[PDB]
Image (cartoon, rainbow, N blue to C red):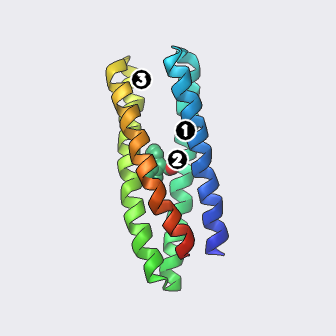
Amino acid sequence: SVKSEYAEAAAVGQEAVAVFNTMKAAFQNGDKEAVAQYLARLASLYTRHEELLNRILEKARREGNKEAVTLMNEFTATFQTGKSIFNAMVAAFKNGDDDSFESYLQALEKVTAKGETLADQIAKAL
Ligand SMILES: O=C(O)C(c1ccccc1)c1ccccc1
């Protein structure tokens, strides 16, 4: 169902949270080789997460679950914010710009954390 497909999406999001927090520890410890690998894994996860969300949104659309569609439109907009901050974070790492990387990392945490409450309402709605 759409509901189980969103449970799967949610788990992938939780994976990225876990990897993000390991990455943050690695950054604080100055282990750049690890961070690079974690950043690559994060991009794969976010790309997967978005694809699962899009298919779930289109399926709630075809099913006429208007309340779910509204919430998912809002969530996928906030997803793009996350994606833009993430991509800038990656670019700062490549550039060797630790102040920006810190800033984008702090800001991405808050986007994600704030996005968690909408995530939970989508669960109940589907
Ligand atoms: O996929 C997620 O778990 C997040 C995310 C993080 C970084 C880049 C893109 C998306 C997220 C955060 C807030 C709202 C929706 C999605």
**Residue drawn at (55%, 28%) of the image:** 23
Asked whether mark 1 lies closer than 8 Å to ligand 1, one says yes
Vertical position of residue 109 compared to residue 121: above or below: above
User: Residue 31, how many percent across, how many down?
Assistant: 55, 15
Please determine whether, in this image, residue 79 is positioned above or below residue 27: below
Q: Are marks 3 and 2 in contact (CB under 8 Å)?
A: no
The residue at which mark 2 appears reads as 46
* Residue 88: image tag: none
Give the quadrant of residue 37: top right
Label 1, on which residue? 42
Residue type beneath disc 1: Leu
Tags 2 and 1 in contact by the CB under 8 Å rule? yes
Q: Amino acid at mark 2?
A: Tyr
SS of the residue under disc 3: helix
- Crowding at dot 1, Cα within 10 Å, few <14 / some 14-19 / many 20+, comes out as many
CA distance separating discs 3 and 2: 18 Å
State the quadrant of the N terminus. Answer: bottom right
3D distance between C-alphas at marks 3 and 1? 14 Å
Neighbour class for label 3 at 10 Å: few (<14), some, many (≥20)?
some
Decide if ligand 1 comes within 8 Å of the CB at mark 2. Answer: yes
Residue 72: name its quadrant: bottom left
